[PDB]
Image (cartoon, rainbow over all chains, first blue to last red):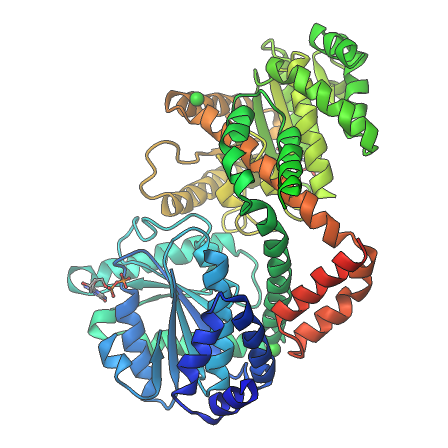
Length: 302
Length: 302
Ligand SMILES: Nc1nc2c(ncn2[C@H]2C[C@H](O)[C@@H](COP(=O)(O)OP(=O)(O)O)O2)c(=O)[nH]1
Ligand SMILES: Nc1nc2c(ncn2[C@H]2C[C@H](O)[C@@H](COP(=O)(O)OP(=O)(O)O)O2)c(=O)[nH]1
Ligand SMILES: [Cl-]
Ligand SMILES: [Cl-]
């Protein structure tokens, strides 16, 4: 019935999909093994989709933009899924589906495989600035979009530094009310910075667009740019290359996390960490000697 | 004579220091243990120094700037060490000392402890864009300086993206000949981008300076800014905080590298990696199943 579940999901059975996602989200070691066989079976039916990441600060307008984009897309014949890695008009529609960082990252990546196997051709993955969540989403999508504020000199308030460089497309949102002209200036400032950061880029220099997600303006143009991104990368053979690299990278991350977890989650290492850290912070112990004691203690109690 | 070596180094014996550095650089497992006791003994004599990282593309003018800065400093009573993580006027002077990423990072960090114990109060650490070398240097210094070109719209040619955000101070070098006016404009462009990236920074927004390292102009002003950096961070209690955090982070990196090495350097894992990677890249195997096989195989042959 792993085979049964896989037949149901790829056939479009709407009841099978949530159950597969639950199987996939199960931390229970016996479910992990079934989940893996199911994914192995569905892997060949996946990949036929554009995965788009969406980030920006609380209140910048991510969920408003996502609802609007999702309707834009549904009306053009797509089947759209929305996941979040920490929208009522959208969630009612039959062609939409709305649903540790290591743990949530893993469950989200596996869930994408199920959704694509189930016929979803657009996958929107939303995140906020929590820990390393932006990098995790950027590493599982084709196109990563950053929403910013439409204020000259203040577009990136509250964004973790380094996040700008993850973006394939940058959007100055809320380009309405008293800020039409200002949004254009704000966009031109970000474009100037992107030109500095990507001075001789030949394939894809991140465009900067304006949008009013609440007035439904610039959404279509945003999606037109997302499609151009895929077309440009596909013509260079880089769309498939990025995916293959992400998958290999993720494989090694899983290896890393498995071996590091043995140490990090050891209760006795947990008990003595503070004092070993205090001793390092105070110059009483070298980092190499603290590291050795951490490994010795893990080994003694594993 | 670990005790003997430690007494000689902290007493200023110029012959002891190179030998300690050689001990520290020894990959031989018996030397590592002596090295650790020596560092433990010298740790309390270290820290009385300003550690400055210097990066930028090949030919931007790093070694020219370093030689000039090092003489500037020697003439002001400092004892200056220069390390490189991949200058003849300087190397002749008695108050100067010129000398795997994980391995070189480790040896450089430990060497800083020896140098500081030996009376060096300025440590300049040079790197280029090789792998993750910039981040490694930024994580072992107090102040990280990025040199760029003095050309409008082309300052960051050849720099890995994300490196700009590591900088505490940015310098447009070669502000001479036909580019005096242009260097000022180039500096103003980078300043604009830094204002965008750090829109509401209250403690330290990276200044952008001009320099002609070959005409010895702007070096003094660069050092004045490096001192201001330390003064500002020290007044906020952040200079010591950054160091303590770097040391703790490095401790855990050593733990990580020790446990991951058991897998990464296993010959049998090395043999089968390509095919397991090929199978992942082709959608024949899930990343989680490839990861499990990697761990199983390491375990079988360790
Ligand atoms: N003026 C203006 N306001 C907007 C726009 N898009 C969203 N908003 C409003 C709706 C909410 O009151 C608030 C936050 O929106 P949201 O969509 O919940 O933001 P987010 O927290 O999901 O990023 O901003 C927009 O395009 N213009
Ligand atoms: N015009 C000009 N040329 C400079 C300046 N500083 C260094 N140079 C020259 C000296 C070398 O010919 C070349 C590269 O300098 P370098 O100091 O070896 O660069 P790097 O590879 O260590 O970064 O550039 C400078 O400030 N102005
Ligand atoms: Cl492609
Ligand atoms: Cl301090």
